[PDB]
Picture 1: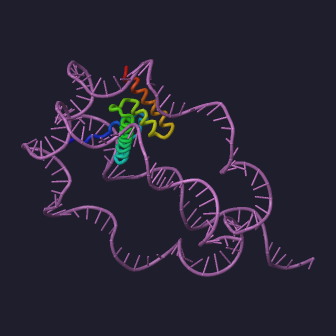
Picture 2: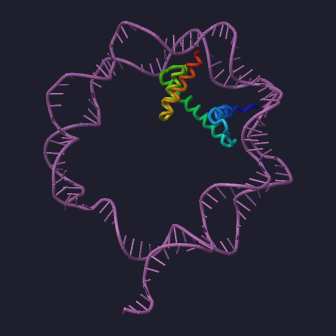
Picture 3: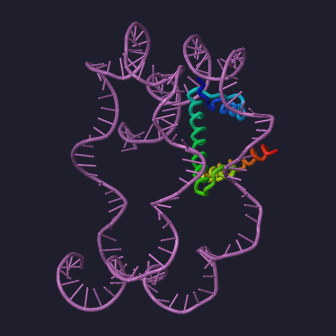
Length: 92
DNA sequence: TGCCGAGGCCGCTCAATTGGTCGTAGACAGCTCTAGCACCGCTTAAACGCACGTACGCGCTGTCCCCCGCGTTTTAACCGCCAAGGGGATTACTCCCTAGTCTCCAGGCACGTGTCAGATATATACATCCTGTGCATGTACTCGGGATATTG
């Protein structure tokens, strides 16, 4: 049966930024772990945020707050400026 | 005087880094998967978000009124130092034992499916438990006066 991983999107993104470069298989497992750790931290914090405010859904703002808590510094104001591109394009 | 003695500049030789070149071996990138099952598109009947006075709760506000802050300097030893001594942390070697490799070999069990049940969800009726409110005392508190402990 199928096992499923993020392994292709990290490779796709590598060819976005370093078109000559590659990854060893052992160094893929790192990205395939890291990328789902940050998934869980955002899901867990966004879940608590909905609960504290006694909502049921989790709209964009329930995540933009979870990113603006969880990320340390310039990464917060960058990631917030990056995600507000994506939904602004999607809703056209 | 003397002598020379003590004195100050320049090619071998060895010993790490540094960068170069050789060749070869899995492991990476990529193809074709093919394959399939998830994403999507397409409806539906759907829940839950949300833009919006008003009762009004409390966040913030204008006063006076005092300790703890604020300021000084003596001193007090705290903290720093240097120098010496002893060993115990260190170095370099030789013998030694096993860590590690590979290879064979089995069955333990983790893996997987095959069925379908006792499980828990959902509704309606409902009674009851639990909250919010209102309400006496009982204590834990702040003070004053004296006894015991301890610092210098």
